Amino acid sequence: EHVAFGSEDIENTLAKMDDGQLDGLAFGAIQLDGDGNILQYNAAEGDITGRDPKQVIGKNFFKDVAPCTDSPEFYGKFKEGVASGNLNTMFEYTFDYQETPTKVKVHMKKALSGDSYWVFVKRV
Ligand SMILES: *C(=O)/C=C/c1ccc(O)cc1
Image 1 (tube, rainbow, N blue to C red):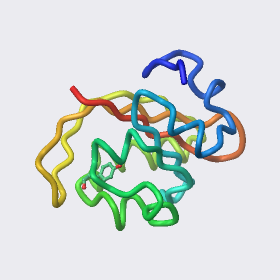
Image 2: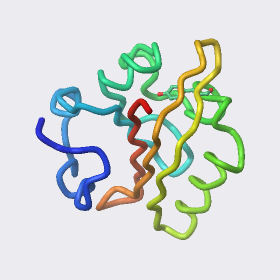
Image 3: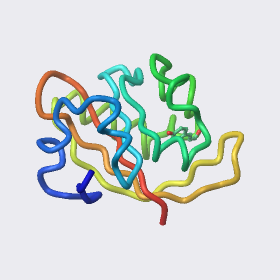
Image 4: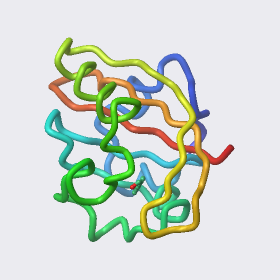
């Protein structure tokens, strides 16, 4: 899939993408509900993090999969952007739960329709 990380219209291009098309992206992509439960999780993300994309869908990202993100700097921004019903934040972060510490760039952005949220990830 020909989509760049950070692109201005990313929520339109990825809108309603199926799991197979999401696996074609150059960067990691996760879709969460407003509680943080994982709806979609692509192959590029699994290659970065080690998680198995099939097994994590349905788990809670903040409570279960990614406790290192349960902090004001990641989860706090997520829950505030959900609450305003609007979210568009980009920041670097380190993933270090049961893995070699890996620094990434994270982009969280509200998905176009409904009440869903994207978490995009690439290495830095
Ligand atoms: C910290 O616990 C980070 C964990 C993590 C980040 C991103 C993922 O896709 C999976 C786990």
